[PDB]
Image: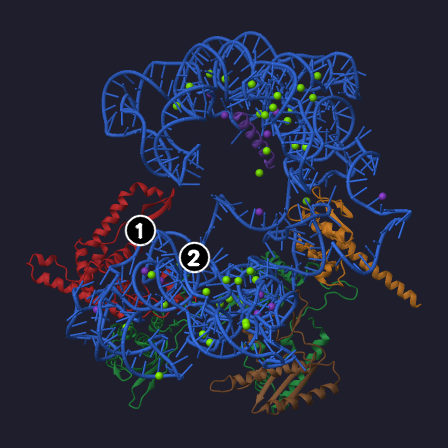
Amino acid sequence: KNVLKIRRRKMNHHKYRKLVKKT
Amino acid sequence: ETYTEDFIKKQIEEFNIGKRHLANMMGEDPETFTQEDIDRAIAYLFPSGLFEKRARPVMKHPEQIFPRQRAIQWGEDGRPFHYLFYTGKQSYYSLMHDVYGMLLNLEKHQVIGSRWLIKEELEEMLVEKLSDLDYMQFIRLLEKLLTSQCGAAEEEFVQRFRRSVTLESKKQLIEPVQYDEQGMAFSKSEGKRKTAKAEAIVYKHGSGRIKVNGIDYQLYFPITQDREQLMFPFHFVDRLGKHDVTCTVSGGGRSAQAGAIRLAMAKALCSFVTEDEVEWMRQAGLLTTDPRVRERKKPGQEGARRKFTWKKR
Amino acid sequence: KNRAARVRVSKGDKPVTYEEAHAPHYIAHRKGWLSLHTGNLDGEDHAAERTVEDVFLRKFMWGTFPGCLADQLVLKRRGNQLEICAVVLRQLSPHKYYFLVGYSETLLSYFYKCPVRLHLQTVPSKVVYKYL
Amino acid sequence: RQFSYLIENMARDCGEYAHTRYFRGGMLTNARLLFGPTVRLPDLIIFLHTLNNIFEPHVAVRDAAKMNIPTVGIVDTNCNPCLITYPVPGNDDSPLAVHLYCRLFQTAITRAKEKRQQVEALYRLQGQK
Amino acid sequence: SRYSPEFKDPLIDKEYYRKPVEELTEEEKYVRELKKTQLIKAAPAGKTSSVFEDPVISKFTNMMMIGGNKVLARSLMIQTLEAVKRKQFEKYHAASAEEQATIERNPYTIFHQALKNCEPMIGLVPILKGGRFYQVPVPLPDRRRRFLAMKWMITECRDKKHQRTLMPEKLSHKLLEAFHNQGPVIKRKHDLHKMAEANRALAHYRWW
RNA sequence: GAUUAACCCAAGUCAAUAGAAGCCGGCGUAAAGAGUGUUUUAGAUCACCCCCUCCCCAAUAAAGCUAAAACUCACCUGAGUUGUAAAAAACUCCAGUUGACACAAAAUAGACUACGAAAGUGGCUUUAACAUAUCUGAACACACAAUAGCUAAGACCCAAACUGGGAUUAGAUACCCCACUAUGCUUAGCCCUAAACCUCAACAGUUAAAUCAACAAAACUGCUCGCCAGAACACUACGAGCCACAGCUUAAAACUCAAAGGACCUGGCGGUGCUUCAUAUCCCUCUAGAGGAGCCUGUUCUGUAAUCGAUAAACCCCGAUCAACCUCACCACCUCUUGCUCAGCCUAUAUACCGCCAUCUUCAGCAAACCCUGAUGAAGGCUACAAAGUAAGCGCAAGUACCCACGUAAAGACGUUAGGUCAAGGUGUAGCCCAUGAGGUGGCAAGAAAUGGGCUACAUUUUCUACCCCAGAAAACUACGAUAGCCCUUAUGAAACUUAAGGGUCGAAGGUGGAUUUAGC
Ligand SMILES: [K+]
Ligand SMILES: [K+]
Ligand SMILES: [K+]
Ligand SMILES: [K+]
Ligand SMILES: [K+]
Ligand SMILES: [K+]
Ligand SMILES: [K+]
Ligand SMILES: [K+]
Ligand SMILES: [K+]
Ligand SMILES: [K+]
Ligand SMILES: [K+]
Ligand SMILES: [K+]
Ligand SMILES: [Mg+2]
Ligand SMILES: [Mg+2]
Ligand SMILES: [Mg+2]
Ligand SMILES: [Mg+2]
Ligand SMILES: [Mg+2]
Ligand SMILES: [Mg+2]
Ligand SMILES: [Mg+2]
Ligand SMILES: [Mg+2]
Ligand SMILES: [Mg+2]
Ligand SMILES: [Mg+2]
Ligand SMILES: [Mg+2]
Ligand SMILES: [Mg+2]
Ligand SMILES: [Mg+2]
Ligand SMILES: [Mg+2]
Ligand SMILES: [Mg+2]
Ligand SMILES: [Mg+2]
Ligand SMILES: [Mg+2]
Ligand SMILES: [Mg+2]
Ligand SMILES: [Mg+2]
Ligand SMILES: [Mg+2]
Ligand SMILES: [Mg+2]
Ligand SMILES: [Mg+2]
Ligand SMILES: [Mg+2]
Ligand SMILES: [Mg+2]
Ligand SMILES: [Mg+2]
Ligand SMILES: [Mg+2]
Ligand SMILES: [Mg+2]
Ligand SMILES: [Mg+2]
Ligand SMILES: [Mg+2]
Ligand SMILES: [Mg+2]
Ligand SMILES: [Mg+2]
Ligand SMILES: [Mg+2]
Ligand SMILES: [Mg+2]
Ligand SMILES: [Mg+2]
Ligand SMILES: [Mg+2]
Ligand SMILES: [Mg+2]
Ligand SMILES: [Mg+2]
């Protein structure tokens, strides 16, 4: 299988961690 | 386009009646009118300049014209005549069966002028279409039959599938030795190099004089390499200073003329040397016409081979 | 890819004549010329005029025998004689073929100021060489 | 192939047909194209070996069933008899077994053809008188 | 080529043919009976059965030929051979009875030895590796060694450093220098050897 | 949208809204077996009968121990060592031999497949020690849970986030090199997360029937618990709990979309593998060139009142085997209106086309009609000691042309690039008709500049003359070198500073040309 569903979650989690760090 | 037996029978009746008509047209005896006469009369009455002869008018016997057709392979009841019909290759496999059967019987009991027929000739003896591997398998089986102690019955069979090939001897032809008014023996030959054409008369006895268009060879050929070419044939057979030559050459340049004379002298000189010496001249390249001639220029390119510059991209 | 005078392969249902089935490189090899005269020989004159006359006669005969021509015309010139040899079909009544022969021979003789003869060979249907 | 020559001769001697060579795709299911629209197919196919040379069922076993042709077949312990109409379990490898089978079928076929002529001939003689 | 593959090259060698039959081996006997059935190409208009034929000089002459002008190329060659011989006769007559023995006066012996003194034993090929081209010392076949010796000699004589000196005088002077292991063509060989030496560590980069 | 006709229903028609219409299906890859094990109340029939893998191999905890390799120290030798596609930085109380010497890690055995609930566990020894004589069962509990991380105190060989330096790069917050810290270790407490996946639940049973969407690790039955119900929002918000305070667990909704998703087939593509090769051909090699100078010619730009088309390979001395007028289609001005034509249009559209072509092709494939395989899916169809293909026709091939049977021409299918051409001619569609048509006069067609192709050169293998290869002269500021410039004459034409030829005058750049690049067997 491709990892396209993982990649969506990967970016969501990355952006969330960065938002939390920024705020 | 299938052709039935009744159709061919009618075509042969027409050819025999027309054969008598054609003989009557030309005022020749219809009884002694051969196929060579038919072809000659048809070429006169229907002149065709088409380069491909197969496209020209023809009046041949139906057997020569029409292709071979296999007859029906089953009767009214629908039963095939041959026990190998359902293979689709009954003629090929019947032959393999016959050759395989002979190889078995031998065990129970115990080149230069001929070649094997090609696939297209086997495909006509059998009247079937064959693969390339089918042809090989059949030949591998015939070769296996020669290596055995094949008898007379097993030799007439193998010869049916062998085609005599006419080897052409490479032995150089020799010109006749002629005699002049004074009784001096001489030979005459000709040579071509590029656009130069030479005719040389080599005398059996002489002092080594060579006349080219009436001129001394060293005055006619001031270039030393052109003179080496004249020396080459006589030097190779150890006959410098033993023959007189009078040759005429036209066309081409100085080098092409020296080459044309070299070939003309060598061919004429073959009349005065031993057969073994003539084969040495042949093997030395002295009796072969050089086929290397100028190639035409093609349109869209600078030369015979050179292309126009591939423009910078 | 070359296109000139090439009937292209199809599904095997298109009947072509012998004339149609041969590309130009077969001219003088497998097929002959449809007009024979002396204008294109070395040292001969009036090739341009013979060419115009030939183009007209082909168009003229196409429309004078509409739907009747089964193959290209063969044009023959001997001296001042002009012979037109045409392969036609057997649909038109013979009376119409005699009318059009008399009409065409006469009209063309006065047009080009030469004795013109028309030779008709009839076939039941267009002769098929192969199905491309 | 050890018995190709034997089997081809047995067929010719009994007046029947043999196909011991490579079997080309569609000899039976596409016979009209390969042979002609009026070609008559076999009424009975006898397999003396039901497997091909890669140890798989001979393609004609399946294709004989497709064309609704009954099949007689010698079926060894490694063969598949499901589609063979009249299977005969027996050794297909030993020359003694294979030779026997050829004698039996050859004899059965030769006797049956002779019987057909006897019956017909008697049926005609009695018909006239 | 206008010769079919069946055509074999002609063998122009008088000795090869006069050789007696008894001396022949069973292999050499087969080749001779075979050629009697083969097609033979016409002899090219260059090489003949002359005893004065030298394949090396004929090859050097062709490498000097510009635009198919063989007459001029041959003229320069014979002028160089004459210029070499005259320079050696002058050195010979001006020398002492002892030195005369060591002075060579045959221009063919000088020409051949001059080229053999310029043939390079090792060569360098460029090899792509790791994004940089590397010069790599590589053995050279004998054909390539002979060609390079000739090409370097002709190239040196065509150099513009020579002002108004004719080719027969330039080439004759370069041959006599190389005959004595001197001159710029010998230096060009030594440089190729020094560059191949300095690139000794890069020999492994070769894969053949 | 209008209009004509038609269709449906009909005193209705049907736009919006709402309702009617849904749980016995699933959980390897589509959503789903919750990281692991163990209850109660219960459920099951797999518990009595009735039976065959107890012990040992790398479970776990504790204590003790060490063979190989490091580090460090010492003596003796060496001047370098380290780093690699190749370098730099770095070290030089450095390196090599020998000896002494671990709170680190655990070759081979292991081609074994064992232990443990899982996580995990493969150096040695010893002690303790691996639940349940039905099964299932706690997300309301309890006890565990790799790596990373936190708190505190220690150890420290080596490795190593971060950081610094070196190098690479347009940049390089990377990949490559060096140094070094947290950290990996121990002790004592936390944290409770993994693609914790063998993505396949426990127990019992079966291999026969329908074997079976595909793929993967064949298809199922009984029973039970857990879980799932379009995508995305969302490992998110809020609430709650927690030694967690940038955390974990549980976990939505609004707005939005007509899909998302799983597995395959075909094709393309891969800085895609292996093998074998290319033959003027990819590299190396061979010869002469282009790229530098002048000139000729095309094109692009700029300019002009003043055409058009081609324009990566496959444009660029191309349509043109050819523009002073004409040609001519352009510009300016003037003139004609059933017009040389039973008109005309070089007006738009080559992305409507015929016609004739480029291109792969310096290819060998295209394909009707059948047959068979795949459960009768998109699709696929060969093995010669042959295993499902048979194949008309087309192309190649063969023949033919040229001097051979060689070579060179010619030929070269189906398709590819909506490739070129409406300006060869013809033509679909649209448009112009006192003008987008027709005619006349005159005129443009240049060069700041750039660029493609070619020509002639830079000379001594040359320059001039004789000759057509046995010569004489020339040879650097009067040499080589313009086919350019200027002047004159001539030729063609009605027309020539303009086109061509010749002569005179003039004697310039150029001194053999970088990266790159063309052709030839
Ligand atoms: K209403
Ligand atoms: K998890
Ligand atoms: K191991
Ligand atoms: K160990
Ligand atoms: K896994
Ligand atoms: K693919
Ligand atoms: K250049
Ligand atoms: K150029
Ligand atoms: K077109
Ligand atoms: K057009
Ligand atoms: K149009
Ligand atoms: K000058
Ligand atoms: Mg993958
Ligand atoms: Mg997102
Ligand atoms: Mg040339
Ligand atoms: Mg072409
Ligand atoms: Mg068996
Ligand atoms: Mg899933
Ligand atoms: Mg699990
Ligand atoms: Mg649990
Ligand atoms: Mg339990
Ligand atoms: Mg943990
Ligand atoms: Mg820790
Ligand atoms: Mg370290
Ligand atoms: Mg540390
Ligand atoms: Mg430890
Ligand atoms: Mg795991
Ligand atoms: Mg899971
Ligand atoms: Mg469970
Ligand atoms: Mg959802
Ligand atoms: Mg998470
Ligand atoms: Mg959260
Ligand atoms: Mg919260
Ligand atoms: Mg090339
Ligand atoms: Mg230039
Ligand atoms: Mg233009
Ligand atoms: Mg354009
Ligand atoms: Mg265009
Ligand atoms: Mg005008
Ligand atoms: Mg004009
Ligand atoms: Mg106009
Ligand atoms: Mg197009
Ligand atoms: Mg040929
Ligand atoms: Mg061609
Ligand atoms: Mg061909
Ligand atoms: Mg286009
Ligand atoms: Mg107008
Ligand atoms: Mg001038
Ligand atoms: Mg005049």
Left or right of B147 on screen, residue C104: right
Report x, y in % for residue E5: 43, 65
State the residue in front, F229 or B46: F229
| Chain painted brown | C
| Chain painted orange | D
Q: Quadrant of the C terminus of chain D?
A: bottom right
Q: Chain of mark 2?
A: B
Report x, y in % for residue D14: 75, 58
State the residue in front, B233 or B219: B219
Q: Chain of mark 1?
A: E
Which residue is rendered at x = 73% and y = 86% of the image? Answer: C96
| Chain painted red | E
What type is the residue that disc 1 sits on? Answer: Leu
What tint does the image give chain B? green
Q: Please say whether residue B156 is visible from this viewpoint.
A: no
Q: Residues within 10 Å of mark 1 (few under 14, many from 20)?
A: some
